[PDB]
Amino acid sequence: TFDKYDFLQAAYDHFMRSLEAFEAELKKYMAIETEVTMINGVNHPLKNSLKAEAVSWKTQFAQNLHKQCSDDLKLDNYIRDLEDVRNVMAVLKVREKESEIDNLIGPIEEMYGLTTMVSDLRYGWKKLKKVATEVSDNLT
Amino acid sequence: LTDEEMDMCRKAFAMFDKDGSGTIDTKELRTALSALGQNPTEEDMFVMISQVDQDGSRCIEFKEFVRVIQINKQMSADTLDAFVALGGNLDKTGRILVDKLRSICEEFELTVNVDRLVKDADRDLNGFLSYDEFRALL
């Protein structure tokens, strides 16, 4: 019954099998954590080593989300900065939905999954208002 | 369920609750674990007691003592010891290797021995012993 837990980039393979389903992935790892705690109530060197292995696994899985979170951040930084057709094409972009998808990916990981870019994320949100101001000045 | 298990249960309950409180408190339990060498945390022992404590007492007693001994014992008399003697290393095959018995008589250094026993416990008359005739040997 300890051997049923014998387990690091296989996690990325699991990610390759793929929104909130990510949260479900973290919670099934949390369920492994809680049945380990119940077995702590049942049983420690052999147990503390796999306890520390859970310390390894969920932190590294959080970081393999966090790297993609950083990529989301930087690729959003990118777009932060016959012309009327281009203005209309950017006017069509649902863009706030993409910013919201990134915001939901980040803040849920920080809070429910528990850098100084949090204020940058806030300036991400206000960025659209600033861009609308710039487009208003671009009207003329 | 039996009558001598009550005897050993009373003796072991005496061993654990050593001061005389009538209830297993955490300190006497850790005293027992530290006599056995273990000094775990003060949060895992809480969970262990909380699974064993049914009454909400934070202290387990003789009814709970025999409840855990009952579940661990009868959940998991003469079948096993005579079974796993040599044939239970074979798991319902009825063919015991002679080399195992030669090894057994090799290691324990016995002065005089002839293996005519297996020659004259041969009830299938082939050169090995099935399990029923193995009990007939015993």
Image: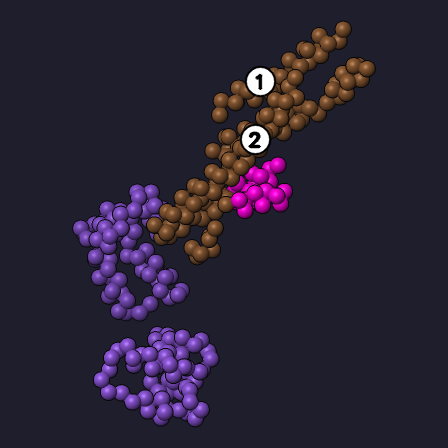
Residue A107 at x, y percent in the picture: 54, 28
The dominant secondary structure in magenta is: helix
Q: Which residue is identified by label 2?
A: A69
Task: Look at the picture and state if A85 lies above or below B110.
Answer: above
Residue A111, given in percent of the width and then of the height, sits at 50, 30
Which amino acid lies under the numbered mark 1 shown in the image of this protein?
Answer: Tyr
Q: For the N terminus of chain B, give its image quadrant.
A: bottom left
Q: Which of the numbered marks, if any, corresponds to residue A123?
A: 1
Residue shown at the point (37%, 61%) measured from the top left? B71
Amino acid type, residue under disc 2 in the picture? Cys
Residue A16, percent across and down? 61, 43
Toward the top, the furthest residue is: A140
User: Residue at 43% across / 77% down in the picture?
Assistant: B90
Q: Is residue B16 left or right of residue A70?
A: left
Q: Name the quarter where the C terminus of chain B is drawn.
A: bottom left
A21 inside magenta stretch: yes
**Front-lying residue, B133 or B57:** B133
Q: Where is residue A62 drawn, in percent x and y?
A: 51, 36
Magenta segment? A9-28
Residue visible at 38% across and 47% down? Answer: A49
Specify the subunit that label 1 lies on. Answer: A
Q: Chain of mark 2?
A: A
Residue furthest to the left in view is: B19
Check the image and report above or below for A62 versus B105: above
Quadrant of the image occupied by residue B62: bottom left
- In this structure image, what is the colour of chain B? purple
Label 1's element? helix
The CA distance from mark 2 to mark 1 is 16 Å
The residue lying at 53 percent from left, 37 percent from top is A64
Please name the color used to draw chain A. Answer: brown
